[PDB]
Image 1: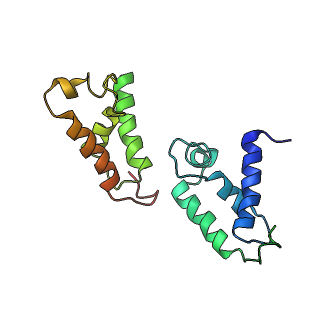
Image 2: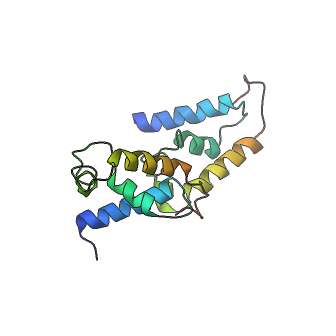
Image 3: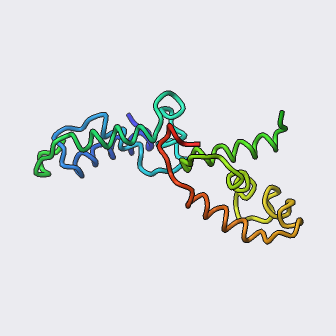
Length: 80
Length: 80
C-alpha cells in the first residue's frame, strides 16, 4: 500500500494522463506528478532525490514536458 | 575558512543564485542571504549591521528581492 505522499503522486500521475488525454500513463506522468510546483524547498521538485542524485531539474522539466507533448491524445474517455 | 554563521550566509547566497537560476552570483544574493525574511529579529537582517548602520533597510529589502526577480533567469547548466 501507499503513504499519503506516494498515493498523491500515483493519483496525480493518473490525473495527468486524463488531463492530457493520454492513452497510457507513463513514467513521464509520474515524473510530472512529482513536479507539482517549481518550489525550491519542495522535495517533489528541488529537494528531490533526482536533483541531488543525478539529473538537474531545469533539464528534468524539459524532459518531462517534451514527452508529455510527444505522447498522443485520445478523446478523454480512453485515457490511461 | 568560514564559521557556521558565515559559511551559512555565503551558502545561502550561492543557493539563491542557483534556485532562481541566475547567470551570476553577486552582492544582491549575499544581501538577500542576509535579508532572509522581513523579520527585524533576524540577526542577519535588521538588528544586524543593516539597520544599525543607517542605510534605509526597506530599500535593501525591496531592491534586493526585486533584483532576485529582475536578474535574468537561466537553464540549470548556466544557473549561478
